[PDB]
Figure 1: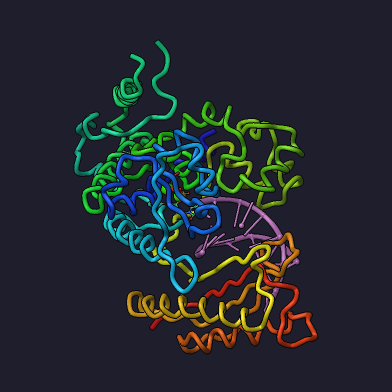
Figure 2 (figure 1 turned 30 degrees about the vertical axis):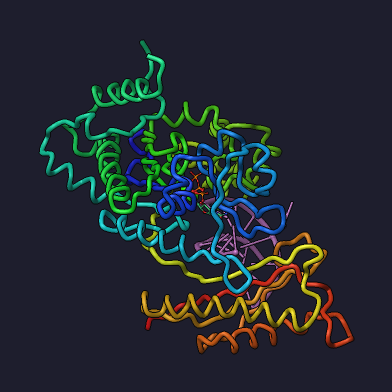
Length: 430
DNA sequence: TATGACGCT
DNA sequence: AGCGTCAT
Ligand SMILES: Nc1ccn([C@H]2C[C@H](O)[C@@H](COP(=O)(O)OP(=O)(O)OP(=O)(O)O)O2)c(=O)n1
Ligand SMILES: [Ca+2]
Ligand SMILES: [Ca+2]
């Protein structure tokens, strides 16, 4: 009863940039602003594959992982920006550099966990305690939360979406609990005020807009962030969880959007995250293993302990390129030349990482996919990485894969390779 | 039809 | 060490 721990100890936020690559291209070319546009890789085959879509283009049905030519059928006016192409492949430097712009601003407020190229988690527990000590005992104005949604509000006893927002926000604040410095709901509100500021700083200093979620753990923050995209942040309180989860498809919770989540649905015979509450921890552990059972048991109650790991920099640096279908590499000269092209971009990126971040990678991993193989990776081998030389790395990458060539005729290469991937890991300080 | 983090064995 | 899962 009192020994019920409710996972309200932390204040955690997930910040995520709205249509990130599109914003980056639109800062650079003002003509793309406020217009249906998408970002594509390559152009010859079907106009290129789309990887990012503005919200105006989304109104027409334009999605990621779609050919530009098909996109132009749903949206004739759609504008396109192309990813920079280097050494025969896509080069994403523009977007990685835009990312450190954002991560460095976010780092001044709290320590972040780089989660992707455009999203970071933030643990605001410490920042919130201090704000509570400066706001003495004085209340929190709705003017401090100009873009915040309180999930599940308004409730109880105006039909444009901004009027709703203030109604729920007023309800939340007018019932707030400012006399207690340990009230979890008051802490989420202070965290939300901090994130409004974080988000105004990112836009002030990059011109990029984002959404955020604020709650007690990474999972809820992440789910919360997506409730009011774009350019809005959503506070998900501990108390909103039973209603929020009662109709939430299990696949929507982070790590349940794949196979494990599908077997939760098929085995247990449920649909929504809330239905998990009727199962005991021992039942769940028998169904899915000690780790999954324990984590499933806590999570449907809104409790999750996976911490915000202080890590602003990737553990891994890698380049890949698919050669699907008839483009599959089928000679020794092809395989070596693309390994060289990949090795060359990787060396460009590693030298920059060494100067910037005072570290060197020590292991090189070569992954390949042969033609006729449902698995995304067919083979993965590693060797030492001792000089940032592209000709050595491509040589070593070949040496460790050459054994995979079926063909007895030595000049050709079978089975044809549909994918090459070089990857620098095992960093050491420098 | 380009990337990164982590678990399991 | 190497494969599998889950995500942006
Ligand atoms: N399968 C993917 C997913 C993402 N990205 C890149 C392009 C995106 O712009 C960026 C961030 O991905 P998101 O999943 O956050 O989606 P967006 O940021 O594009 O838009 P939004 O978050 O508003 O949906 O990462 C990619 O190249 N391939
Ligand atoms: Ca995003
Ligand atoms: Ca994202």
